[PDB]
Image (spheres, coloured by chain):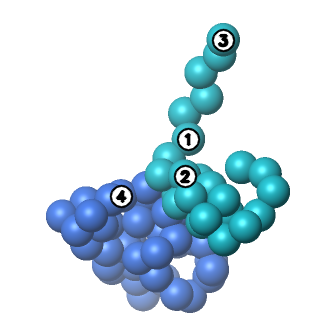
Amino acid sequence: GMTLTPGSKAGVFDFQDPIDIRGARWAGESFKALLFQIDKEAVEIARQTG
Amino acid sequence: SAYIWCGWWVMDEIQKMTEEGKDWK
């Protein structure tokens, strides 16, 4: 839904797809691109739940 | 010449094409 990254797989965040991790490389780049995902939904709950 | 910014994921594909016996990269 609203939290897709348009080139994503819609429901899986996998560190091997460069679009999900935003082109990140090695670890400190890649893992931190999860911490952006886990925000992006925690924000989106605030829309639906109100 | 020109300049196209490509990440290493294209170069991961390209170094996987030519090292597995493919034809273009």
Residue at the far top: name it. Answer: B1
For the residues beneath circles 4 and 2, the answer to whether they share a chain is no
The crowding category of the residue bearing disc 3, from other C-alpha atoms within 10 Å (few below 14, some 14 to 19, many at least 20), is few
Residue at the far right: name it. Answer: B23
N-terminal-most mark, 1 or 2: 1
**In this rendering, the label closer to the viewer, 1 or 3:** 3
Front residue of A15/A2: it is: A15
Front residue of A47/A40: it is: A40
Image position, residue A30 (x, y; %): 30, 67
**In this rendering, the label closer to the viewer, 1 or 2:** 2
Q: Which residue is mark 3?
A: B1
**Labelled pair 1, 2 in contact (Cβ < 8 Å):** yes
Q: Which tint is chain A?
A: blue
Q: Which residue is mark 1?
A: B6
Q: CA distance from mark 4 to mark 1?
A: 13 Å
**In this rendering, the label closer to the viewer, 3 or 4:** 3
**Labelled pair 4, 2 in contact (Cβ < 8 Å):** no
Q: Which mark is residue B11?
A: 2
**Labelled pair 3, 2 in contact (Cβ < 8 Å):** no
Chain in cyan, by letter, is B
Image position, residue B23 (x, y; %): 81, 57
Chain hosting mark 2: B
